[PDB]
């Protein structure tokens, strides 16, 4: 720690922590190790153990400096840079793998990896525990500590790894993904980009600079005390740090951070700031502008907001837009998190929304989504993208467990509404062969459930006897 990094201590409040972030973000190289330790320290005493808490856990310089010393001693002790000559001011694959091994070999032999509050370097030092993306972050913090300015965090919507080397063009796995998959640490991500999985976003993943890595640790704050309770202090801190980053420009290329800020603003709006909808739309604009509109979550964030607000029309449109992105992916081994999300939207969330909409229609609601043929078209476009996703995939998506919910959802719209959508080869065009073959079935007053099921699962036969 340099003299200038120390002058704000002790940190006595949320605003003092924000001041420290502002100061670091004004430097050439914000100090990831310092910032992650401070966040982990304040999170430990606001969410993990609040015994004795009277306002805010004061972070004394002595305490934080000792944690920082533990981390830098561990890294500098274990990684001898003389063994890994740096040409071009760039790092080698062997050096990146060594740092990843140092972090990985340090971790407790046995612990649940999905635990809360194991994301920061405070957890690494005090508990020898990190979650999956926490290991990638720690590798980047260790590399910055070692002077390796070219090593940066790479992020998809469900995984993390690093970029490094000449022009920052090399990739390396540094952590695990999911449960029960084989370690691939040290390898590139080329095979996953080549196979067009969601996990590697067809190459349209985030390549962070240092300020984006600060944004990542701020998104990683976890205000959860337990299932029913959040720390208001940590929510306020995370929200203020995100606004600080937004104002500086460091969320411009970070759609998920914008969605996370929008969500926070929905919970507790900051006077004089953009509405949550404005922020969700900024996250989609970021995904279009910087990532070829190949991210799924910007539309999921927007749809979730509309769903909570029971804006059925806008929620369906945003889920249809979500499906329009996924249709150009192949469903691969390790994409299960986004399959679970689509399955929940199709098979639980939409059915519950339309069920309430049907009750409200019975009670004489006007302008109901269930009487709007554009909403029926959004529902059909959502299924169309899911069917098209499945085409050419190494792993199928649909099965009969989806068919009953599709028949129920279609049936929530009366035949006179459904008839008004023109399906062309309100107007809708299908991309998937499954939906094209279903077109015939979509306007009958009583939908043919068995034929729908046959078409959705492309199952060959009916029952023998
Ligand atoms: F690094 C990994 F491996 F953990 C991948 C990352 C995830 C993630 C994130 N998330 C994940 C998505 N997430 C969502 N919460 N709601 C979502 C939506 F379904 F409503 F869209 S998506 C929480 C924040 N937020 C900022 N940055 C990142 S980087």
Image (cartoon, rainbow, N blue to C red):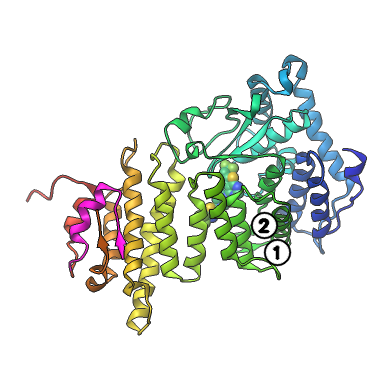
Cα distance between the residues tagged 2 and 1: 7 Å
Tell me whether the residue at label 2 lies in contact with that at label 1, contact meaning CB atoms closer than 8 angstroms.
yes
| Residue at image coords 51%, 52% | 297
Q: Is residue 107 visible?
A: no
- Residue found farthest to the left: 465
85 to the left or right of 110: right
Does residue 440 show up magenta in the picture? Answer: yes
| Residue at image coords 20%, 66% | 443
| Mark identifier at residue 223 | 2
Q: For the magenta stretch, what is the residue range? A: 426-444
Q: Is residue 422 visible?
A: yes
Considering depth in this image, is 256 or 406 the residue closer to the camera?
256
Answer few, some or many: residues within 10 Å of disc 1's Cα (few below 14, many 20 plus, some between 14 and 19).
Answer: some
| Residue at image coords 51%, 60% | 302
| Residue at image coords 48%, 45% | 294
Does residue 175 show up magenta in the picture? Answer: no
185 to the left or right of 38: left
Above or below — where is 265 with respect to 203?
below
Can you tell which quarter of the image residue 374 is in?
bottom left
SS for callout 2:
loop
What residue is pinned by disc 1? 232
Considering depth in this image, is 270 or 249 the residue closer to the camera?
249
On-image quarter of the N terminus:
top right
- Which percent across, then down, holds residue 26? 81, 46
Precedes in sequence: disc 2 or disc 1: 2
Can you tell which quarter of the image residue 18 is in?
bottom right
């Amino acid at each position: 720690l340099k003299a200038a990094q120390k002058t704000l201590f002790p940190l006595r409040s949320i605003d003092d922590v924000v001041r420290l972030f502002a100061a670091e973000l004004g430097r050439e190289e914000p100090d990831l190790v310092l910032l992650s330790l401070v966040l982990g320290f304040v999170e430990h005493f606001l969410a993990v153990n609040r015994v004795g808490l009277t306002y805010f856990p004061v972070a004394d310089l002595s305490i934080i400096a000792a944690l920082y010393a533990r981390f830098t001693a561990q890294i500098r002790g274990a990684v001898d840079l003389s063994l890994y000559p740096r040409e071009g001011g760039v790092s080698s694959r062997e050096l990146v793998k060594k740092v990843s091994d140092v972090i990985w070999n340090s971790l407790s032999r046995s612990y649940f990896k999905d635990r809360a509050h194991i994301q920061s370097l405070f957890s690494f030092i005090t508990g020898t525990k990190l979650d999956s993306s926490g290991v990638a972050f720690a590798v980047v913090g260790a590399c910055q500590a070692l002077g390796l300015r070219d090593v940066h965090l790479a992020l998809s919507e469900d995984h993390a790894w690093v970029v490094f080397g000449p022009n920052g063009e090399q990739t390396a796995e540094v952590t695990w993904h999911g449960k029960g998959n084989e370690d691939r640490r040290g390898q590139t991500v080329n095979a996953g980009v080549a196979e067009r999985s969601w996990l590697y976003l067809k190459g349209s993943y985030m390549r962070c600079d240092r300020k984006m890595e600060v944004a990542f640790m701020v998104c990683a704050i976890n205000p959860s005390i337990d299932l029913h309770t959040d720390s208001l202090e940590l929510l306020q801190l995370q929200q203020k740090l995100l606004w600080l980053l937004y104002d500086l420009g460091h969320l411009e290329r970070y759609p998920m951070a914008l969605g996370n800020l929008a969500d926070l603003e929905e919970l507790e709006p900051t006077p004089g700031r953009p509405d949550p909808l404005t922020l969700y739309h900024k996250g989609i604009a970021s995904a279009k502008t910087y990532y070829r509109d190949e991210h799924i979550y910007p539309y999921m964030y927007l749809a979730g907001y509309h769903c909570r607000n029971r804006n059925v029309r806008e929620a369906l449109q945003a889920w249809a837009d979500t499906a329009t992105v996924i249709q150009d992916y192949n469903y691969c081994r390790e994409d299960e998190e986004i399959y679970k999300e689509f399955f929940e939207v199709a098979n639980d969330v939409i059915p519950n929304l339309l069920k309430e909409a049907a009750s409200l229609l019975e009670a004489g609601s006007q302008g109901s989504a269930l009487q709007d043929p554009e909403c029926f078209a959004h529902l059909l476009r959502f299924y169309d993208g899911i069917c098209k996703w499945e085409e050419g995939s190494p792993t199928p998506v649909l099965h009969v467990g989806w068919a009953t919910f599709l028949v129920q959802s279609l049936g929530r719209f009366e035949g006179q509404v459904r008839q008004k959508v023109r399906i062309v080869s309100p107007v809708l065009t299908f991309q998937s062969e499954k939906m094209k073959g279903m077109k015939e079935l979509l306007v009958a007053t009583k939908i043919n459930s068995s034929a729908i099921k046959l078409q959705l699962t492309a199952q060959s036969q009916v029952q023998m006897k």
